[PDB]
Image (cartoon, coloured by chain):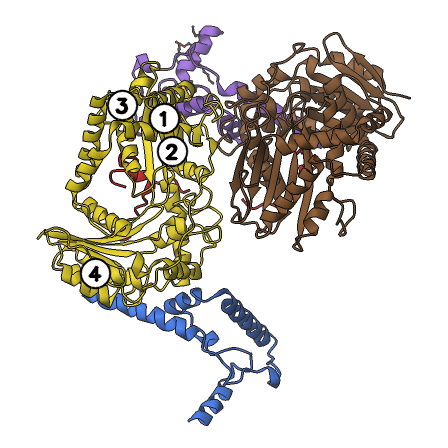
Chain colours: A blue, B yellow, C red, D brown, E purple
């Protein structure tokens, strides 16, 4: 399962643009709240990675293979911050039903 | 049911009174005022005061706010330069979860960075609302010019420090001043036992004595604020007695002799020696009173004047001259007896209400660890005698003064002229 | 601050109620020594201070 | 040729020098600084300084701007606490209409209310640009804490007075201080005759001596404003001599002995007894100099320090100790000779430029009505002798000090500790 | 000519709405500059008079005859301020012409 997940990570292809997994999340309301709660350096790296991926997609290029994002290396930075947004979101919801 | 004041081993001073009241009140008192900051973390206590509804380890901000409003209870934070007090009140059937919320807020905050980043704008708004009146600004200026390090720190956050207070400063302040030896949990309308059980599930883990504050040093001086207001506000104080001395009782008798607020609506507060000494010479509208603020290491006593800019000078002089008369022994025993009656009636009406009673017990706890029955006080105030009052006066008339003035100060005198 | 200050109490006691006229909505400019300041402003010449 | 002077019977001083320069300058000097306001019209001189391009009775605003820019000339306003100076400069073939514009601006303003209402936002912008650096704020604070009434008035308008300065206040200030007995018209590169002939078209309206200004009174006091700047800009001054008194010079020799500032770029070290006394103990970056500001009734002399907040204390102490050594006679004659050479070279390089020469002549005119040849001064500075310098020092070392501090002032000392 | 001007002033009919003459000027650029230069009390009276005239035109009424604006009484307040606007305007124009 670990090797097949690495093979699917190579087949997804966002590592060839230098992106992380959390860069590829669709910005819903909860995702934008999690992005807003990021520290400044992580937010700046995320915006630069997104801009570089957009530029590479503009020129129809990819990064060189040494510059790709290694599956093992990818960091799920937004995840911790996101869970909270969802948790808080759900809590408010249940309370609504009260 | 006399307060069952009891000091848990750690240092927390638990106290309670089962008044069998419909609405109870539970407060927690910490020696964590604004005097415990230094020049590197100014305004941290203001953000800590405004950060009582933040996410805690045990309850979120949404859960705390909706749970306190669900039972209709109230959570408030009152802060002086020495002490902070977090108070909850509500129906007896909901004070278990009210103590859950309050003790979570006191003991286990999280201080998330996005929450404090949202709170700094509220800090600016609260400071503007607080400085909408001239008395607050002139007392903050008076403390800043009167003291050097400890009591000179403002209750409200400075303008440059907004945007600079971090989560780490709040965590450091809480970890260094919210310890069990500086805390008293006081409950009116609750059983003492429960206070203790909540005092072990909470309030017992942080048990150091914390970070000791610096001794406050007097400096003297005068700070003036020309801002074109219609009325000139001026406070002239000097160093006085601290908490825990009979000279503090003498200074309280001295402010009630000089005048400490009107008792009659639209009265002229006839008796106030100050008010009489101003009104015999000036027909302009005015408001002259005696100011006394005593903290556990130092006190400030002086005069407070509001007047028309033009007369601002001699009115201040007249008020000052009246205190000099009291420094020369020019007083009558009936006036001192009336001052004692005014002071003791003010104390009894201050403790007549439930939240004032809870605050008093709280303060006494942190200050002396003991409860002083209202009766005891009455006989101690009586202890103050005429000469004692005179003595405190001479202290004021001699000690270097500190002057905070604001308004159109073209005719407001200086300290070397005063 | 119950017997010590009385009327002056509310000046020394913030009381943020937390849960449970109003404030009236309370600049970036374009970019040492010792000598008495001397301000200068010109009709077209940008202003300056030579302290 | 040489400088040539006439005192007109209405009191106006006319000074001219024809050196056949290609660009000629003409300035007009009035004793109408910020010291002539009181608490009711603070900031009026700032708006008057910024209101030099407003529609004048003689010329509409459009012309007063398009006509000066059409010939490429320059109109500027420089203001101290005592004096205002309106200066125009341009080609000799256009200085007739330049004198028309300048004398219309000085003598016959209109001060329309919509124009000053538009100018108050520019007043706020100019104050922000001026207080972008710490020196300006600390010198304004130092003057405000050092003096009581006259020289304590700020050069820049206070924040509350914006929006409150009216046309009537500007008209009253002009009618009470822009009179012929307080004015000198100084022209480099022009014939004296024309200045005399341009002094009749205007400068004839107000022949009074103006509303004289109150005598400035010293107050002392120390003000500290935590602002965050890592550097604690601290100025500690005392009362010193007036411009005229011989002691004055002695104080100028004393600041050039204790350092007059840097004389080398990026390498200005060990240029001061002060700088040496700080640098022998502190390895942090610093900037210590001597401050001297003398006006026609009173002067301020002291030390100015910029330093890291932490070392701010002992550095200030070290600088203070150095002055005490000069107060004990611990000085050498070669050091005083080098200080005299530095002072006279600074004076000659100040008067070597055309606008500095025009300002100097102007100042001398208003101050003493006479021109003092650069040579004369040189021998008077030489008159100052070693003991004289020592004397001025003891004046500073003893006289009540006034202290303006800004930055992170947790380790900045007070006056009673200093 | 004076009596015929009073008759034309009655025939114009803006005095029956309580208006002044300078209230009836069309707000061009010069007129708005002259209105902006008015003092606060004159501007407030002008705005109240215009609002009252608009309300009276809404209800198709006029003022009672004792409340009309007497020709003799009408004050040309905006006029002084207006001339200047025009003068300044022309001066600027001339400068550009030349
Ligand atoms: C068929 C197409 C043309 C129709 C035109 C109809 C016009 C109707 C409105 C004007 C006539 C109103 C009734 C005529 C008699 C008016 C008498 C009167 O009281 O008004 C006076 C005025 C002449 O004014 P005057 O004599 O100079 O001095 C006035 C003070 N004594 O009297 C007049 O000025 C009356 C003449 C006005 C002419 C205006 C022409 C405009 C073109």
Q: Secondary structure at mark 3?
A: loop
Which mark is on residue B99?
4
Instruction: Look at discs 4 and 3 and give the one toward the viewer.
Output: 3
Tell me: D307 left or right of B323.
right
Instruction: Look at discs 2 and 4 and give the one toward the viewer.
Output: 4
Residue located at (66% from left, 43% from top): D319
Instruction: Look at discs 3 and 1 and give the one toward the viewer.
Output: 3
Mark 4 belongs to chain: B
Report, in whole angstroms, how far the alpha carbon at label 4 lies from the one at label 3. 45 Å
Circle 2 sits on which residue? B134
Q: Which of disc 3 and disc 4 is earlier in sequence?
A: 4
**Residues flagged by tags 4 and 1 on a common chain:** yes
Q: Which of disc 1 and disc 3 is earlier in sequence?
A: 3
Please tell me how crowded label 1 is: few (under 14), some (14-19), or many (20+) other residues with Cα within 10 Å. many
Mark 1 belongs to chain: B
Circle 3 sits on which residue? B272
Circle 1 sits on which residue? B306
Q: Nearer the viewer, residue B177 or D40?
A: B177
Report, in whole angstroms, how far the alpha carbon at label 2 lies from the one at label 1. 10 Å
Q: Secondary structure at mark 4?
A: helix
Q: Which of disc 3 and disc 2 is earlier in sequence?
A: 2
């Amino acid at each position: 399962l670990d090797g097949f997940r690495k093979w699917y990570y190579n087949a997804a292809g966002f590592n060839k643009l230098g992106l992380m997994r959390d860069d590829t999340l669709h910005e819903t309301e909860d995702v934008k709240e999690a992005i807003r709660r990021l520290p400044e350096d992580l937010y700046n790296d995320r915006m630069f990675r997104i801009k570089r991926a957009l530029d590479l997609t503009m020129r129809h290029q990819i990064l060189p293979k040494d510059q790709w994002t290694k599956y093992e290396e990818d960091k799920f930075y937004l995840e911790p911050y996101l869970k909270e947004v969802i948790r808080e979101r759900k809590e408010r919801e249940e309370w609504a039903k009260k | 049911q006399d307060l069952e004041f009891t000091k848990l081993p750690n240092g927390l001073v638990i106290a309670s009174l089962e008044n069998y009241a419909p609405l109870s009140r539970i407060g927690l008192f910490v020696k964590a005022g604004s005097r415990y900051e230094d020049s590197n973390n100014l305004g941290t206590s203001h953000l800590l005061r405004l950060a009582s509804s933040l996410t805690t380890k045990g309850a979120s901000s949404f859960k705390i706010t909706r749970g306190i409003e669900a039972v209709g209870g109230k959570l408030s934070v009152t802060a002086t330069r020495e002490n902070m007090a977090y108070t909850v009140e509500g129906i007896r059937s909901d004070i278990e979860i009210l103590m859950e919320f309050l003790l979570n807020v006191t003991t286990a905050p999280e201080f998330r960075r996005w929450e404090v980043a949202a709170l700094r704008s509220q800090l600016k708004i609260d400071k503007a609302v607080a400085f909408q009146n001239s008395q607050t600004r002139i007392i903050e200026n008076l403390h800043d010019v009167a003291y050097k390090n400890a009591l000179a720190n403002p209750l409200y956050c400075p303008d440059y420090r907004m945007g600079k207070i971090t989560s780490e400063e709040l965590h450091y302040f809480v970890q260094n001043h919210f310890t069990s030896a500086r805390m008293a949990l006081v409950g009116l309308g609750v059983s003492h036992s429960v206070l203790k059980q909540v005092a072990e599930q909470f309030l017992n883990m942080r048990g150091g004595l914390g970070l000791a504050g610096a001794k406050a040093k007097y400096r003297g001086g005068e700070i003036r604020e020309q801002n074109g207001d219609n009325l000139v506000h001026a406070a002239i104080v000097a160093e006085s007695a601290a908490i825990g001395n009979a000279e503090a009782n003498a200074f309280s008798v001295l402010q009630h002799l000089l005048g400490a607020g009107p008792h009659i609506k639209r009265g002229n507060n006839t008796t106030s020696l100050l008010s009489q000494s101003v009104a015999k010479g000036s027909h302009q509208p005015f408001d002259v009173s005696a100011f006394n603020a005593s903290y556990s290491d130092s006190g400030l006593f002086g005069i407070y004047t509001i007047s028309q800019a033009a007369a601002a000078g001699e009115v201040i002089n007249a008020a000052y001259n009246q205190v000099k008369a009291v420094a020369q022994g020019n007083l009558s025993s009936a006036d001192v007896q009336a001052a004692k009656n005014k002071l003791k009636a003010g104390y009894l009406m201050s403790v007549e209400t439930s939240e004032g009673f809870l605050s008093e017990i709280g303060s006494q706890a942190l200050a002396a660890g003991s409860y002083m029955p209202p009766s005891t006080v009455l006989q101690q105030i009586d202890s103050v005698a005429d000469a004692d009052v005179v003595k405190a006066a001479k202290k004021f008339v001699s000690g270097k003064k500190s002057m905070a003035a604001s308004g159109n100060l073209g005719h407001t005198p200086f300290l070397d002229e005063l | 601050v119950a017997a010590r200050s009385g009327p002056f109490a509310p000046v020394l006691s913030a009381t943020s109620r937390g849960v449970a006229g109003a404030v009236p909505a309370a600049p970036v400019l374009d970019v040492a020594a010792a000598r008495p300041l001397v301000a200068t402003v010109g009709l077209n010449v940008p202003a300056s201070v030579r302290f």
